[PDB]
Length: 54
Length: 54
Image (cartoon, rainbow over all chains, first blue to last red; front, side, top):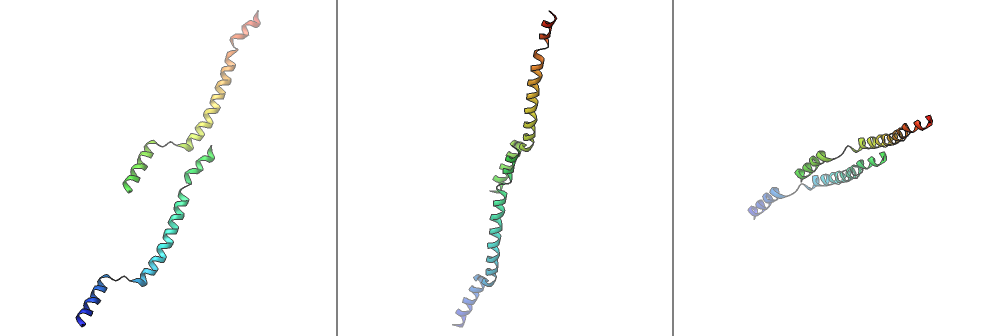
């Protein structure tokens, strides 16, 4: 019984995620995706200023 | 995907026009055309003055 509990703890150490850090990484990745989509929305229309010359 | 975007940027640099310069070239070429038309209209009557001598 102790041996099976040790193997379960070892498999969990081999695989289990660090969720307390995963919360911060997710909260940062959301802001990164939002800044990236806003940057793409800025990039889309810079060529369009050429119409002002004509 | 990166290589395809790079090839698109490369072929575009091979082909894409300097449109901002093209606006100035257009605005100048129109004026040069109208000055050429006025120059031809002035050139038309130079022989015609000989009739005044008779």
